[PDB]
Amino acid sequence: LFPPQWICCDIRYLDVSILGKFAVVMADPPWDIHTLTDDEMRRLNIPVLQDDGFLFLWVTGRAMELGRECLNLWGYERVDEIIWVKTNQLQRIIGHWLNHGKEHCLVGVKGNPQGFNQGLDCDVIVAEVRSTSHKPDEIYGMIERLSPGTRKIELFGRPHNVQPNWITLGNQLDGIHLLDPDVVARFKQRYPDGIISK
Amino acid sequence: NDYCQHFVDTGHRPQNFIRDELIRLKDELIAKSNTPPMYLQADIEAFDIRELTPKFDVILLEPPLEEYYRETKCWTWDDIMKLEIDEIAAPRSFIFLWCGSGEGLDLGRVCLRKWGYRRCEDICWIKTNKNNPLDPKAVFQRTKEHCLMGIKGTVDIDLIITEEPEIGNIEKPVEIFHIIEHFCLGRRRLHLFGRDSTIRPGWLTVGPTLTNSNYNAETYASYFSAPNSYLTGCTE
Ligand SMILES: CNc1cc(N2CCC[C@@](O)(CNC(=O)c3ccc(CN4CCC(C)CC4)cc3)C2)ncn1
Ligand SMILES: [Mg+2]
Ligand SMILES: [Mg+2]
Ligand SMILES: [Mg+2]
Ligand SMILES: [Mg+2]
Image 1: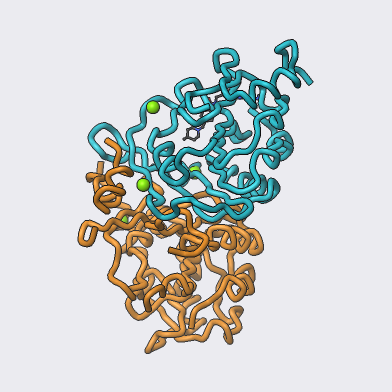
Image 2: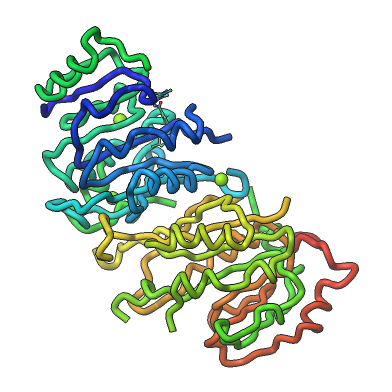
């Protein structure tokens, strides 16, 4: 359970029913802006992943609107929106009309989550831009304080995103690495030969 | 390092720790081009918006939301969505809609679409708390407000950082006017739900709490009749 787990896969075709239920879902999708088409995004089997809990959905450009669509489509209500203010190592700030100083993360809720620590953190992140397309590590702290110890799943993560209590899905991860006994069982039953295709 | 952990430890919001050519010509040409301030007391709920002519190049829309009075007439998004904004917007024009930080982030986007705009920017007003270290649905402590920019028809960053105003003070940062003005979108600029305290050269202010009016549609239109009809507001 607790240590990092991941699955190299195409999230369009993985049968995520084998993974169980999660208290938090995070997704950093490759939106078709300026890649997954809008219809592929809509059809992701997000709804099987949670009964009660929160989704964190990174958005940019016209995905600020499309991501709201998917959010409601998948059965969530948007109840918050986090912005990461991007700075340099000296704590200064680093889509025509305006230059962009921030990235947006929608926060959706599904069901009636209980036992979460709402209101410990504020809705702003100030953190240094490390690598291009590298999300700030503070989000995992906010998410852990919000729901400590619970199961979490990240979609479209990269190898640097693997964290304890998290399962990371992405098409540039190194193989399959699963340790939760229930997951390992249902993965073997669904994929006896270790291949993920249709 | 981790300013979110630091905010949990001390109560200093992460934005407290943000630090810090010549776009002065723009602002000087704005000033030479600006019309005199015009303003009109009007109960916008009961007011036929079509009497505000000519069509506007820019609309700043600042409805008084209940969330602005937490510990202190409020407009709901129901009221706001029913404004006939499309009837006064020029066929190419821009809107800036203050949406708060709750459901307005969604309902203000429905408004923009209803009035025929597409959202091109999301301007965040990030409020620091250096001088003083929840909604039921909230997951996090809300320390910002959003002003959505919309465009219909065919310099600056999208962040404003200021100290959080005192309780009961509903003013938005005057920085929003510089962002709008720096665009040079045209000279017909309308501020709906402005106040005595927001009246400004280059702008027609309309709101219920204004104590005086000087608006005259013919006088106002004379500011933009030939040869002045298409100036950006950033020329001689
Ligand atoms: C075809 N189906 C796929 C596709 C797929 N991916 C496609 C290939 C890369 C992938 O593997 C790793 N994700 C990224 O690199 C990635 C990185 C950055 C961003 C944008 N961010 C926005 C928010 C900000 C905090 C950070 C910037 C978006 C994605 C994901 N993974 C599984 N199935
Ligand atoms: Mg933009
Ligand atoms: Mg990192
Ligand atoms: Mg924070
Ligand atoms: Mg200026």
